[PDB]
Image (cartoon, coloured by chain):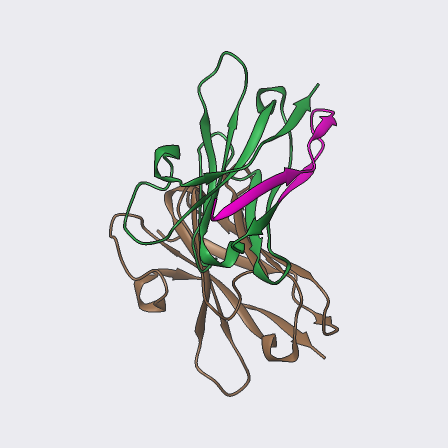
Chain colours: A brown, B green
Amino acid sequence: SEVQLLESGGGLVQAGDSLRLSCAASGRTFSAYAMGWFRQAPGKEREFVAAISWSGNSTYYADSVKGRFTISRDNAKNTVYLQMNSLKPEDTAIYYCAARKPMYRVDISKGQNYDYWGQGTQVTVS
Amino acid sequence: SEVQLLESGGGLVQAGDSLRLSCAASGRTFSAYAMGWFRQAPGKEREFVAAISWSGNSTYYADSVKGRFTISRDNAKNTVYLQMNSLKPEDTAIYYCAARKPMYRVDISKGQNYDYWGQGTQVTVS
């Protein structure tokens, strides 16, 4: 079995706006997983955005979003959130949520260390 | 002192409300330091609340407040913030912002590892 992940909240927004993305887990218990957001811009490779420990007691951000984005989770609702403030055109991307087992202390910024992925939600900043 | 800290935003709130505290700095600016928030109520030991790293790319939270509180920093405005959602009467306390010179690996949840402290702002949750 696999955790199933479904991202939501993407759409078209204007430069300077905020947008909150969310990812709902099913199939498997969400508190069993540490979570990460990644994003892929048009024509580029996927890149790390943010990560949160299984309980939500520790977060980590890429330098390109720190201070503007906040990752959080609510395990009692199987949801992890990415609050994006002060958006710019360069933040245009498909945004993915990924899950990994906390068993292994890894480079939490590398997608290869995550085991399960959502389908992506697209965000377009004009 | 190298740096003096002054917190604001406390007050009386109803359970379930939110509040954002802030801390201002004079002397050396916040950009030189890692920061944390602590709290203490009469008759109780001082408790660690949240920490933010020197560069602002990592945060760490006590289990008592994870998922409800967010620590952030705005160097340009020389300010650190603690956003508190879903407040409970157990949250009532004087909240203190502390600074640490970011030179060594230490336990960021221990007040003894901090170097500079504000005067505190009182939060009361009915």
Total tally of numbered discs in the picture: 0
Asked if the magenta segment contains residue B21, the reply would be yes
Q: Which residue lies furthest to the top in this view?
A: B43
Q: Residue furthest front?
A: B1
Closer to us: A90 or B21: B21
Query: Residue sitting at 43 percent across and 56 percent down?
Result: B54
Closer to us: B39 or B25: B25
Asked if the magenta segment contains residue B10, the reply would be yes
* Position of residue A7 in the picture relative to residue A109 (left or right): right
Question: Image quarter for residue A55?
Answer: top left
Q: As displayed, is residue A51 above or below residue A74?
A: below
Region rendered in magenta: B1-23
Q: As displayed, is residue A87 above or below residue A98?
A: below
Can residue B32 be seen at all in this image of the molecule? yes
In the image, residue A80 lies at what x, y percent? 53, 50
In the image, residue B26 lies at what x, y percent? 59, 50
In the image, residue A81 lies at what x, y percent? 57, 53
In the image, residue A119 lies at what x, y percent? 51, 66
Closer to us: B84 or B11: B11
Q: As displayed, is residue B66 above or below residue A96?
A: above
Query: Residue sitting at 69 percent across and 69 percent down?
Result: A11
Q: Which residue lies furthest to the bottom in this view?
A: A43
Can residue A81 be seen at all in this image of the molecule? no
Q: As displayed, is residue B96 above or below residue A36?
A: above
Question: Image quarter for residue B93?
Answer: top right
* Position of residue A18 in the picture relative to residue B41 (left or right): right
Dominant SS of magenta comes to strand
Closer to us: A94 or B95: B95
Query: Residue sitting at 44 percent across and 76 percent down?
Result: A46
Q: Quadrant of the C terminus of chain B?
A: top right
